[PDB]
Length: 56
Length: 223
Ligand SMILES: [Ca+2]
Image (cartoon, rainbow over all chains, first blue to last red; front, side, top):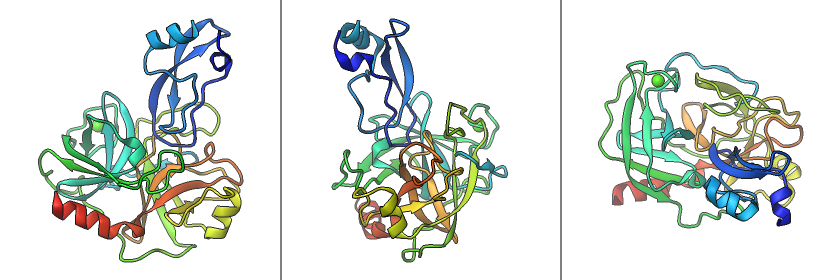
């Protein structure tokens, strides 16, 4: 699978509270995390389906 | 808000919560029909909740109003966060009272050293996650621009101001964005960004509201 799928979730410097999905390789599944609102990394999805399709 | 204290019930009447299913940002009521927040808090659909204290319990003083117009600053940069400010026009004017009041726009730019009040329902931990039910408050000073720049080399513009402590411990955090920084009864800052929360050498960075008073007034009068 792509390398960005193995990176930990990135909240970013912004201080909003936006729920996004990320692939947790250690668990082998997509989970939610708090995204700050700006400068998102690639392991950041708006849905679990898109997350699993890209990093599954 | 990390290292703060629970605000006295309805002691920050101008504070609002931006909700699109759950609380995601804060804001400030500047007049009966307009709220100011951070541009990175943009969402196509936004419900504004006023008169709040406990964000998870219906208390009876709350007013829920949908946003009719969402206007971000035309020069907002999603990468550098320069001009991180946005205006929201409500569907209908709110009823102003003790729990719901407006905050005055700046008469001028407050100098470094000015004590201010920051508030929000954001994370209260620097490490880990603890979302408060009750509105949190924090007393903190505007920091000298040179210290702000030394903390964030080459990332601070004239439209930003650092507020907090260079030793860390107290700061705004995720969930606080768009919230107010009030000094002497005037809105001088808007929670925007920072590296982590309450970390040493990295105090919160805020939008310098005194640079946008005219843009705010011109936009309000034109919409
Ligand atoms: Ca409530």
